[PDB]
Amino acid sequence: GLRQYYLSKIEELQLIVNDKSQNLRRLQAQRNELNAKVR
Amino acid sequence: DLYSRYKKLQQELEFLEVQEEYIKDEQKNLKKEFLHAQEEVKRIQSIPLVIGQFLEAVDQNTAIVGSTTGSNYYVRILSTIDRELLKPNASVALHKHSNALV
Amino acid sequence: GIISLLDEDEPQLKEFALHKLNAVVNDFWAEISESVDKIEVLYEDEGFRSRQFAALVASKVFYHLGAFEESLNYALGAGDLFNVNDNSEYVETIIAKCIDHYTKQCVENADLPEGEKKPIDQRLEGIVNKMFQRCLDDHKYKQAIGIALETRR
Amino acid sequence: MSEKKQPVDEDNWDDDNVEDDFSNQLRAELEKHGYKMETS
Amino acid sequence: VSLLSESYNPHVRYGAAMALGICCAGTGNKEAINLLEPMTNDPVNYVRQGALIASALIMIQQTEITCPKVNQFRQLYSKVINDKHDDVMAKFGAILAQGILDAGGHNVTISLQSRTGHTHMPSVVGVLVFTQFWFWFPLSHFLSLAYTPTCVIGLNKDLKMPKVQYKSNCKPSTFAYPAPLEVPPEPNFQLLDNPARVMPAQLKVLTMPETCRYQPFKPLSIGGIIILKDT
Amino acid sequence: PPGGGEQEPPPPPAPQDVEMKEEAATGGGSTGEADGKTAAAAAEHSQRELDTVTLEDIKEHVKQLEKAVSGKEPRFVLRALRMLPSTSRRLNHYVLYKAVQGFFTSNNATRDFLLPFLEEPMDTEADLQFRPRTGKAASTPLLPEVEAYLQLLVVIFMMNSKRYKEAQKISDDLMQKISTQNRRALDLVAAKCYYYHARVYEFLDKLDVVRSFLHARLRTATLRHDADGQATLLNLLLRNYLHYSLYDQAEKLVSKSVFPEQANNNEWARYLYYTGRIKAIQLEYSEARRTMTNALRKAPQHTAVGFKQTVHKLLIVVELLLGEIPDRLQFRQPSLKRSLMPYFLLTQAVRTGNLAKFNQVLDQFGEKFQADGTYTLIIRLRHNVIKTGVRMISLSYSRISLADIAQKLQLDSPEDAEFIVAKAIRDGVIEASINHEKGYVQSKEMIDIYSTREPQLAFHQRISFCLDIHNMSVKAMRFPPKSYNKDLESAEERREREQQDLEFAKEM
């Protein structure tokens, strides 16, 4: 099924997008402060 | 089209996995990099050192001193100096040319 | 309460027990969810006429408790009683694992098809081209252009 | 904010510990000792 | 790579600019020009240089309507080449960026890529060999393999030029020219001969010849040469 | 009529004044910024929706003369609310019914007139696809009926209005809830309507149908989306099963949705209490007094009479089961004067070593402890009373006869006071021997428990945890780090002046 096998795979991935994305968002500015201290 | 909606979306997880580990390298990488720079700056406090006397600061970490040559100056300072070691009337150290706190 | 008579040793009260496992599978579904799982007992038993429906309701209850491939093996071995209905919010639960293990196995079958291939339980590929003909006949060809890639065939 | 669904509807604390220990015990000593003088 | 534009070394800060310059050079990438805008400001001469190289590669054959930073930068290369106090490495990207930026009379362009999907490998070798001007100056003179035209060509026999004159439909200011100044009511129906230049973004805005004697047997989508059937 | 005519006509426009800017702004933002734009980044209409609960909790009481809420329903139910060219007249229609309340008379909605205020999913192009509009425009009349409740000819109006909102809820359960907060935005509306639903349609009506409807609501939960349906559908599942004795405590053990992942500190806070009383009735072994304590410390500043009385009582009820007891009545705000006196009077007996003093409580307030229904947990405390006594005496005296402790503990039998003492040895508690032939129970002096490695464990429990709360004071800290635009080294033009004057001194 496309509606009921395949659309069941959009519902799962987006959760990993939104939080691993957010962890990256925290970590990059956490590096960026240190880059400011470096230069 | 529904078909690209899952393949192109796992495409960017497949892309996304190489960013948090990659800057997780940089949590330590600019530590071990930064400490090269950290002790590096103190070369100016070599040995040809002339003496001033601290007077006051405009702000944080930029100040005004009274030289033993008699004249006074608006100078900069080394960051590692504990600033709370300053001001009885502080005997300070000046660079002989660039004329800043040592 | 009906769980208490799963030791009758008369192959009519297993049938009567599974009479009450589809209409009332929302209240003491909570009850027989972790305690009793004797589906495979009569399912592997020589006692027939009552194992066909037994793997359906285990595929119901083990689905919601994370025993997904447990619901997928019983989903395959449940038979004609299992795939007879596609008019629920439950066919969505079972083909989500069937076509899953299908195509994630078919990546390895894109690796090495020749030798150590799939022992298909004859519906694991059967509902593939079945519902794929539903794609061919329900006018959707932006997906009939796509699941024909999903099979990697 | 604070919707808080309703299924139903010092000066104090040193006084509360001495309330805990000093709870139900004879309450009125001026006479207890003066009556233990001759009995005890 | 914009994150890598702020490396604490000017080497990775330098190579970030050439990374954009090899990525988006076919496009008038407004984002990439936006990133390359402060890249000329750096106190390092060679990253100021490579800022001008990537700033030259981003906008060839682009006249003011793909992005307005074209003439913002034409004054800038003269602005840095006409100073005496600059570095020779600094204005070197400007005297370089002129011959880049006005290459072939706006008739040749870069293309690491066919319309088919296949990359153009002598342009690929031309740009990779173009990167190593560091250790040999005419080593990056190997660049002529990257220069590719943007022109349709009509044809009917093995040799004979046809006489086709089609036109365009969209906003005609896209057909702007360099137009040098030399100090001592609007037509969208641009008639073209057989060797006529056209932007690849202007391959969609043209009109097919429907009234001429000639009619293209091929659907006109790419430039280059095609058979143009005499009807 | 001057008295009504001078205090009654200002009520109508000033609630209209706040309702054209709170939920007409929720009308302009929760329908155009959630059904059309992202609300996960901008979920302010959730807490704004909380505010449109809170103001309306204590906003309406009266039977609404002058049509100050009763004329809102003929006003606010005639809504297309399709798009801005169809709502630019609706913004006038927020004003046009003020002339219907004021110039004319409106329809006085008084226990009878809700039926022509309900059948508008059709009137002037109303829809069901904007269920951020139709669920808010469901709730927005589904609240003020059922807020005061009006159980007199209001249960069927409430009921049918719940039927219409349930048609919206089935369109939510079936029809395009993906990434719209159709599911998520109406899990708050669904969740909050479960309580009015549960305060007309639970105790007055049959809840056990809402059991299977709630199992289906949980079935469609956790598949399509795992937030906001993983949360409310479990305390809202729990609240009558606790009141019942159904098996679903062990089902709650084997449940996957035991974590709903940061359930908004209200359902999440009370949730730990709702699982605390689970192991209370299933025999607290000091496991859940931390989840009672945790449920307490996650609870807000509103009033204690809600549930904070009962976690304040039951939280220690399980530690009276252990034997430990603090002073409870230390914060006499609105909780430590009213509802304690039987229950502190209980632990007043527990802090004694007296036996039938417990009975002198247990007859005095046996019914008060049955008013809450804790009495089956109350009934088992004689064990901890007598272990309190034997630790007390066994700590106090050393070589004491067993023919004294039955009399002092008013046990009325020394012959089994060999056996209560004997099992006090058996179960752990006290160690040393009874000269059962003689009758004295000797006890040894066990000092220097320090070099006994118990307080190292009393550390290491707290070493690890205190390191953890430093770690959380780190992990909660680093969200601030932002607006760090440019680490400018020195300059450019002043660097050109530095090389310029440097070139002057270099030629010099």
Image (cartoon, coloured by chain):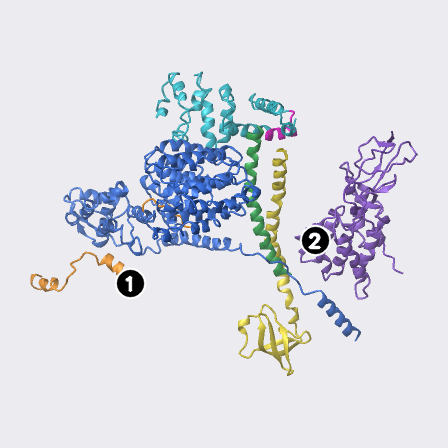
Chain colours: A green, B yellow, C cyan, D orange, E purple, F blue
Residue under disc 2 on the same chain as residue under disc 1: no
Relative image position of residue E59 (x, y in whole percent): 77, 50
Q: State which region is magenta.
A: C103-114
Residue F377 against residue C44 in the figure, above or below? below
**The C terminus of chain C appears in which quarter of the rendering?**
top right
Relative image position of residue E168 (x, y in whole percent): 80, 40
- Which secondary structure lies at badge 1? loop
Is residue C112 one of those drawn in magenta? Answer: yes
Q: Which mark is residue E34?
A: 2
Relative image position of residue B83 (x, y in whole percent): 55, 71
Chain for disc number 1: D
Residue at 15%, 42% in the rendered image: F415
Amino acid tagged 1: Asp
Q: Nearer the viewer, residue D36 or E23?
A: E23
Q: Are marks 2 and 1 in contact (CB under 8 Å)?
A: no
Relative image position of residue D21 (x, y in whole percent): 23, 57
Marks 2 and 1 sit apart, C-alpha to C-alpha, by 67 Å
Is residue F224 one of those drawn in magenta? Answer: no
Left or right side of F267 for F174? right
